[PDB]
Image (tube, rainbow, N blue to C red):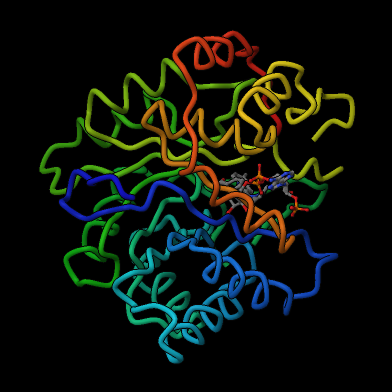
Length: 298
Ligand SMILES: NC(=O)c1ccc[n+]([C@@H]2O[C@H](COP(=O)([O-])OP(=O)(O)OC[C@H]3O[C@@H](n4cnc5c(N)ncnc54)[C@H](OP(=O)(O)O)[C@@H]3O)[C@@H](O)[C@H]2O)c1
Ligand SMILES: Cc1ccc2[nH]c(C(=O)N3CC=CCC3)cc2c1
């Protein structure tokens, strides 16, 4: 159950989100990643930022070693943090994530964000106050292309890019590889349909994060509506006899969007893979489309 990427690699269309806030002890990511792979998840999303690549890699290696999966059947994503946008740091940042996970390659490496930060996770000046750096994203992308040339990243992509930022790269002279994907916040309240049409037009897969309405970490307005209590999602839930989460994920699959889903809960993890068992009608799809309201959680 995969989509073919513009470099000829395959990405599974449902993936497991691995971020948990720092209140969650690290070991938890080991345990939940194992459960995710047991339930049928094969695409696993992590990042230097999440401080979990050691535990996530252990869960992957544990399931490889006991024969539960082959390495070739796992799609593991990691991402380049913004203090490493300088080109000479890009391959060493990837190599560090590889050391931590003890994996030989990542299936996908992404530029985590278009923003550049002072090299050194969040460098802060004398009053606050994040220290930005000016780095041409196109020169970061070229160092990204070398990681794919080297086989350290099977596929390379971007995250949190808008259409102009995508075009900075697509319009680059001497361009060797398109990004395979643009991983962005995308759910029924902020559906990105304009960005989606753009990405489809360039054969770039859109990958939705916060598809279930985010973890609402209080560091996210607590007044924002709660996506999974949306009366449309719940009316669809009862009509199809699934849940609001599953309606939200299935909407993404039928629009050609690859969809992530974080859960640190055993039943919810198993539940999320039911997304392949049912479909939404065109009229369902249309009701969900009607929910777009430009609500940004993150
Ligand atoms: N590239 C980026 O900048 C970026 C940004 C944000 C996220 N991401 C990636 O995307 C992943 C997912 O996004 P996210 O962390 O915002 O969360 P999300 O997938 O929108 O999940 C939100 C919450 O949904 C709950 N949930 C999951 N399945 C459910 C179900 N069947 N019924 C009810 N509730 C359910 C989970 O809580 P429980 O844990 O309690 O089940 C989870 O906290 C992240 O983990 C990370 O891998 C990337
Ligand atoms: C400046 C900047 C840009 C993109 C970013 N993305 C994330 C991220 O990936 N998070 C935080 C929220 C939910 C799960 C994981 C943090 C972050 C910070």
